[PDB]
Image 1 (cartoon, rainbow, N blue to C red):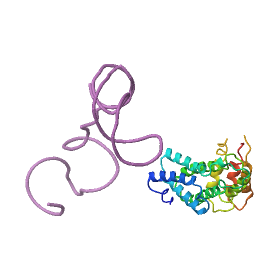
Image 2: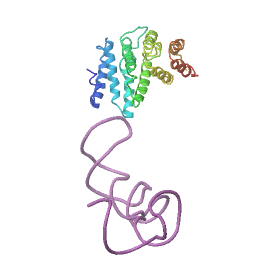
Image 3: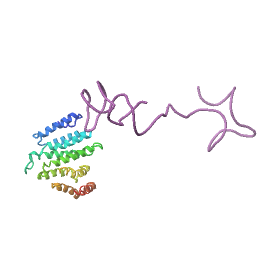
Image 4: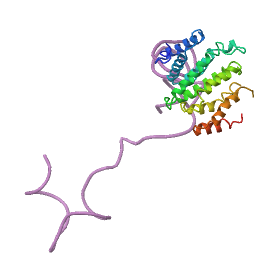
Length: 220
RNA sequence: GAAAUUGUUGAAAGGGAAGGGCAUUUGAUCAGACAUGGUGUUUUGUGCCCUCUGCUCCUUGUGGGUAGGGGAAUCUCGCAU
């Protein structure tokens, strides 16, 4: 498998396992189904960052773990009012599991490696984000993708998600929004989600007041 | 080879009590640095220094160890005078 090669204790078989995962992601004929296989892939990539300690190789590794949303379903096919055709259909299963992995992991990360996963989740939100598609508009990708962002990670009507990751997404999605390079994009519907969180009672004050200051106070 | 206790020697005290506490003098006596620089300039001379050529352990850059020559006319980078 790849969960034993990405979670190895050897550096060389983890780099070679990443390159065989590059060939495995450009071998698109086998990644057709089975959500939990993608969940296991993101758990192996989670450990594959977890063994990297030095700052320059962990930034190279975060950049290429973001780039794995780019090799897997590159934009070139560039579908026309084509709903979800083998570059956008399976991609969403590669996104959700990542957030699911972080939804499983936010207790179990210590005070010295948590910067790696703040920076990692910065790069990965920027990269899915960059692959809405090559352009920032694909409409059923926007509402289906925003349903498979809304329905898991900024739920904020469920306490099952850990409250540090939506406030970190609030801290990063503006600068990493405008890393895409004043234009008009489906941003506001995204912001409507946060307005839903301000509309949602039966929550804690932090989500309610920290997005209500941090996200809405931005003049951009 | 402890104390009680005994002798000798030395010191001290003693007009019908000593030993104790607070404080001090006198007499006797013991402590009391193989401490020695620090800083800023200037001769030189070396090296892990500059430069030429390398070799080797491993993990991510912000690596480590270790040879052969040359060169101070630049360099305090360090250490010696």
